[PDB]
Length: 209
Length: 195
Ligand SMILES: N[C@@H](CCC(=O)N[C@@H](CS)C(=O)NCC(=O)O)C(=O)O
Image (tube, each protein chain N blue to C red):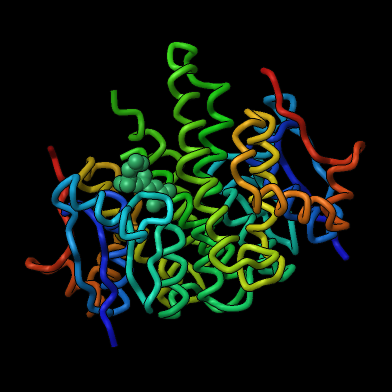
């Protein structure tokens, strides 16, 4: 149809979850990366970032900014936002937890090394004692293939993405969570997901800058 | 009909934008205040806090945590989430900006208020001239904006000076029946909670 246009840096950052979500829906997208501060300025001065911030995604004729507005729109567009408002309630709740933990991990490489260590022991604690139990349970509470409504939703993709970053951050943390482990392989082998895990894709590595 | 039951500290904090949204929808709600560290532990152990955190709202026989999930649900149940995906994208975009500025409230946020966020929302109101931000109908984000404008006034009523459309907007939404009721003394609306 039309190709969405991701305006971000050449990094994971706040844009990766949208790349993932677009990828899982089988939606090809292009990116204009931002390397020069003038690019960001040329975007600001041209009236493209409502709050003068990236991420920003051109899609169906909008200059959508703010991560969550992007993710919600894409998810509704390609029926990754569930069946009804009660399922979106489960989806939003799950996604927001996933976001909290992700934010905690990606920010460890940013904080003062003053506190790297204890904030690291925090993320690991939260990973193993709060968030992973919470989603291991959800899979065990209903014993189904997906998080919500027994069919693929945006939050399955979010969780897989998080499971990938947990493994990077510390692969040991996953071993006491069997369903998530089964869930990870299940979702990883969905066609559009497998395609995105493949080398050469728009998927982004952990940056060092 | 069971009232939504809001589980939070007796404070503004992360629960206030929900109190606002319920009140602007004219929905009566009840509050169970976490008073003791023992109160929160027995919410966790009863299995009511999926991520061991509040805000938690009991609504329609389920226990919702995560503010955005709570707000999204309420806004959808009561037709404050706009009319289609494209209005939700405006509503989400506006709300998430409003949520960021609210978050910031040295005192750096005066600049962002005056030079980034408030110009953005005056321009929204300039663009279509209509009474509400989105779809020429009251939506949740009108209520979030009014809420932001109230806290900006508390922060520094001089930041509202240059923004005549926001000003009329504030007064205009303040005077909605359901809104006026929540602004009245004696409502569940919360103060800035000091210490
Ligand atoms: N993203 C969550 C954050 C919730 C949150 O930070 N809750 C605090 C209360 S204001 C809490 O229960 N903290 C206890 C803890 O984190 O251990 C939301 O928006 O609801």
